[PDB]
Image (cartoon, rainbow, N blue to C red; front, side, top):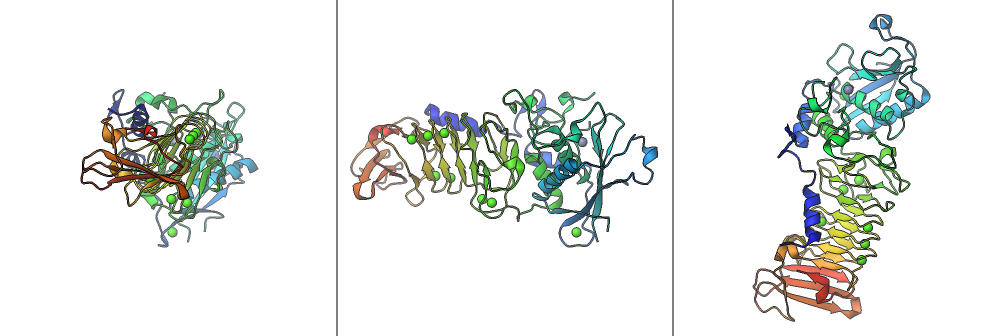
Length: 455
Ligand SMILES: [Ca+2]
Ligand SMILES: [Ca+2]
Ligand SMILES: [Ca+2]
Ligand SMILES: [Ca+2]
Ligand SMILES: [Ca+2]
Ligand SMILES: [Ca+2]
Ligand SMILES: [Ca+2]
Ligand SMILES: [Ca+2]
Ligand SMILES: [Zn+2]
């Protein structure tokens, strides 16, 4: 008993729900359950000088360490200049989210020390690291030989960069999501894939995400939604990161390669961690149909891909700009600025007084409950175009319709449409409860007609 516009919003908002169903015999785990699974060894660095932060030093080894030859690791080599630069962006991506700092220098008052280097012999792997409770705590080692060259050219979005972020995650105390010729079949929970954690080994295709674009597949460079909860559980959240207004995506002001898009063919795979301010997800440069959800902990389908963008638990992102495609935009309980751009968009501000822009195209502004837009905290539709855009109240009315009148009559379902020509301001007031006063209000820039309302 709802329009198709509201059903699309509602289906998308629950599409990646977790924790309440099986997937092919595996239990779906919430983010908090994963945070405990990823930290189940109990190993972590300690705050030895009690200053409230894990302060670690690291060194790119230039010579084989003491005892290296008996390790069975083959030829030693130091990191190249490109491996160092990438390793520093990976370390920064972890320090952004949790209260751990990494400074290049000799083991000195440090809570711990890390080393990075290359080896040539394969022992079953591309790279390996030790947890912080081991006698080789802080070490991580990367394979480089004539048959495996991926670690020589790490770059944003490729597996060499992901491998760095992943091995640093182990040096911080994170384990693989499962105790692992293993495959996704050995996963313990359904979300053990690289759409939720960079610690997993399994392709995101197992959980349905589409990360491939123009024939090629990508890898998240930085910690993903579950990784952020796991490392924040060990060391605390870093609330100073990006604490002023920030833009992610196109026109990014985040200053991180994995949060920036500069063309419509870019493959973004990221989870947003942000410590404060009035922030915007800007995806205006894509022309594919996108589905954008501002709810904390949720996933969006951006740039022609699916399940590739998420917002970390605990973060409030306020604004979102869609692209030239027909998009879905879901706001959260704060006051949001939501812009559809070209295309026929469906926009749902949710709680709070939102500022809605449909852009060109026939857009639908969707209202799922009376508290979405009340006389004291009413949405405004800034570019309402009568005859083209629609205001949709069917989730509330269940298609019972409205009674349009000039003054409240005292019956539930009465509605008044007015227009103030000197300020070019329209409004829709509805008395859903029936006491002859408005319980619901939406305002617009531009006249609104009775036929622009779906109820
Ligand atoms: Ca410390
Ligand atoms: Ca911010
Ligand atoms: Ca914010
Ligand atoms: Ca659009
Ligand atoms: Ca809102
Ligand atoms: Ca539009
Ligand atoms: Ca429009
Ligand atoms: Ca609202
Ligand atoms: Zn690993």
